[PDB]
Length: 49
Length: 48
Image 1 (cartoon, helix red, strand yellow):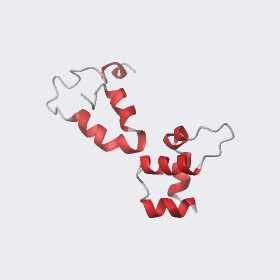
Image 2 (spheres, rainbow over the protein chains, first blue to last red):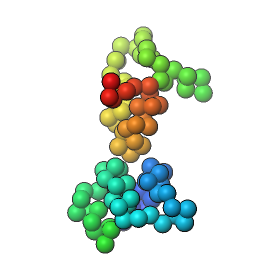
Image 3 (cartoon, chains in turn red, green):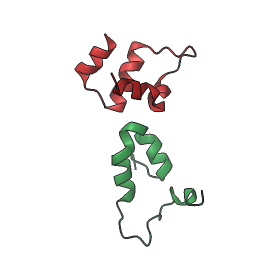
């Protein structure tokens, strides 16, 4: 929960972010986490939850 | 600012002997900032 703050601050994940409101979809979030590679699959599922 | 000109040139490491500089940079910073972005910055083509 510190690395997630860092990642949301990061611009690479904001590239996956597309909605003008700034809210991202579940699939886009999953893809952005996978691209960053900081989190493994189970972790990604947890932060999605 | 001037060095920005040489990043994507094919022969950037002409005098310095380390010929794997671009590959090392790509492997080091590809994940966080994007392999495609790094390759575009350094003028290298992974498909090629």
